Image: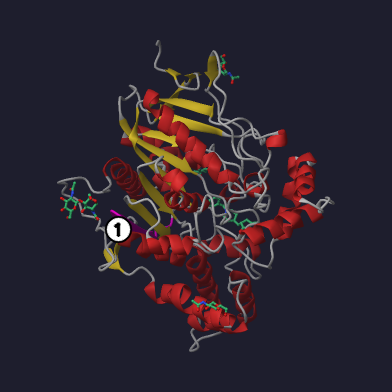
Amino acid sequence: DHSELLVNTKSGKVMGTRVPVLSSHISAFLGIPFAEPPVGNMRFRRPEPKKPWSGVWNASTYPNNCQQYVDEQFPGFSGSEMWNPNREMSEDCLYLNIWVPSPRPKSTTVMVWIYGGGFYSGSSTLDVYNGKYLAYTEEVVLVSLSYRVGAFGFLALHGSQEAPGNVGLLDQRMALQWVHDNIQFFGGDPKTVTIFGESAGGASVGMHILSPGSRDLFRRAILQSGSPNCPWASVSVAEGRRRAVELGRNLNCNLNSDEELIHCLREKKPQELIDVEWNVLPFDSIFRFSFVPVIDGEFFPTSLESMLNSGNFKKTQILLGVNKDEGSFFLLYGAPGFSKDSESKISREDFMSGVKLSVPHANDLGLDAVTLQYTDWMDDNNGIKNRDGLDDIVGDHNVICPLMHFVNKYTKFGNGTYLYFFNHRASNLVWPEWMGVIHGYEIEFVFGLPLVKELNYTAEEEALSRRIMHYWATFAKTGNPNEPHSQESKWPLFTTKEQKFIDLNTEPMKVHQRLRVQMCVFWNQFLPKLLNAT
Ligand SMILES: *[C@@H]1O[C@H](CO)[C@@H](O[C@@H]2O[C@H](CO)[C@@H](O)[C@H](O)[C@H]2NC(C)=O)[C@H](O)[C@H]1NC(C)=O
Ligand SMILES: COc1cc2c(cc1OC)C(=O)[C@H](CC1CCN(Cc3ccccc3)CC1)C2
Ligand SMILES: *[C@@H]1O[C@H](CO)[C@@H](O)[C@H](O)[C@H]1NC(C)=O
Ligand SMILES: *[C@@H]1O[C@H](CO)[C@@H](O)[C@H](O)[C@H]1NC(C)=O
Ligand SMILES: *[C@@H]1O[C@H](CO)[C@@H](O)[C@H](O)[C@H]1NC(C)=O
């Protein structure tokens, strides 16, 4: 061995770079391949392990981002472009980034970030995902993987070995397997690996907790604004097939067999599949994505619900939670009456239209049931109440409630649960006030962006970010976000009986119980029974 930026792994030697972080410095190994480029005949196929390389791999720069749809709704607007690919897109995108504190540790806690983006997008190279602040502040080895999104990572034709589906999830598993096998050489503890992600990434984390082929590869898990049982997180094999065939019809493909559909989809250029990607949705809706994980019977032995009921999942500690206004982002992009530059006061007519889009798989009685649940008949023509009520509908149906279901089901067999409710609006948030505490805006606090003075955050927002970063890191290290024998306020353990959680904001810690039970009893217990009877 030689320098601190030189690591000899089971795959080969890797050369990193010294990165500046808050006056100090740490190491960074960017763009390390954990799989063979899924290009050509391997498109849609399961990931193959990266053949070991000879010589030194240059890991000083960020890798390419996977082929995905690019947000062009508000050009120049940072609020929407901060989520867009900041590196060149390519199908050769299966790489991982590692931030190692300096001096290189011997055996410290490891955290693997799994980005979100509805399974149709996302990048590990984003600014809000820069793990250098967390790695440095909390003294952890921050890893951020990457996986194929869109059709490339989730096209599903059950029965076929050329495109079985869930390969995007297998990409994550191979990265986790690479972390299990090589993180030791970077000073990380393979015995203490915490996987954490947001939205689609949080659902992925929960999917790895459920899938037996992924359970042994990590210790603990953190789920942010995401759950494996989210209505948008997965589809049946029949629906996945239907969407795959529909994708082919949109590209003038031969649909007589799977062998011919796939051959066609493989000859087409990346952007060709992306341009027609949305055309396969079965309904006119919001918070719904085309190619997502499928219940194949392999990655997922049986239905997610049956697995959750039987305790068929990894027993360990989990830390999860949701943001206050999760639905705003989606109403702004597809619901009539919403716009980035207006207060977006919603009319009774637009409210009814919003409900239709929010619960696509519902009939008329179901639509009336949802409306009844979120309507104040004493003041039904209130524009602000209609706007906020619709925001609650999208967030509760798509994020909050399904997560609350997973929380209650998991805790019964689990070994420790910690629930949070992030309800703080960043003072420098570029999005309109009507959106509130937006889906994905806790990430900046998790990654410690508020510590960087040049980002215009307040003092209390830095204190909050430091508090959150420490909760996450301490939990990853021990299984409890609370510092042993500390004088600070204690974050209660979530139990099947008490059901406690905390608010994650700038004010002193406050403890509550039964996070949105009123609305979630409706979404998890009543509505599904109503739609089922009719
Ligand atoms: C998490 O799992 C650990 C290990 O199984 C539990 O600790 C045991 O708890 C039982 C009952 O209180 C004790 O009799 C054992 O002595 C404990 N074992 C150890 C090694 O400490 C722990 O209770 C579980 N925590 C939760 C919240 O379920
Ligand atoms: C056709 O185009 C469509 C475009 C979009 C949707 C549906 C569509 O059709 C149905 C959505 O539902 C997306 C709406 C936003 C959701 C939040 N993200 C940013 C973010 C990224 C990663 C984690 C957290 C936040 C920006 C787009 C975009
Ligand atoms: C790639 O490696 C070279 C040295 O071989 C060095 O300039 C740096 O680490 C990387 N250069 C570029 C342009 O990415
Ligand atoms: C911080 O404030 C300055 C002055 O208004 C502005 O120009 C800059 O863009 C802001 N930085 C960020 C990251 O918003
Ligand atoms: C769901 O609906 C189907 C069709 O009506 C019915 O056979 C089944 O029993 C229902 N499930 C429950 C739990 O009621």
Question: In the shown orientation, is residue 446 left or right of residue 39?
Answer: left
- Is 252 situated above or below 533? above
Q: Is residue 379 above or below residue 54?
A: below
Camera-nearest residue between 463 and 301: 301
Give whichever of 471, 385 is nearer the camera: 471
Front-most of residues 23 and 260: 260
User: Can you tell which quarter of the image residue 250 is in?
Assistant: bottom right
Identity of the residue furthest to the bottom in this view:
378
Residue ID at (34%, 56%): 504
Q: Residues within 10 Å of mark 1 (few under 14, many from 20)?
A: few
Whole-percent x, y for residue 263 in the image: 78, 42
Residue 114, horizontal then vertical, whole percent: 48, 44
Q: Is residue 73 left or right of residue 412?
A: right
- Say if the magenta span includes residue 156: no
**Residue 144 in sight:** no
Residue 13: x percent and y percent?
49, 17
Vertical placement of residue 391 versus 123, above or below: below
Using the rendered view, name the quadrant where residue 508 is placed. Answer: bottom left
* Callout 1: SS: loop
Residue annotated with mark 1: 507
Q: Residue at x 38, y 40 (%)?
A: 451
On screen, residue 326 versus residue 88, left or right, reads left
Q: Position of residue 497 (x, y in %)?
A: 26, 68
Of residues 170 and 318, the one nearer the viewer is: 170
Which quadrant is the C terminus positioned in? bottom right
**Residue situated furthest front in the rendering:** 159
Please report the bounds of the magenta region as a residue range: 414-425
- Most extreme residue toward the top is 2
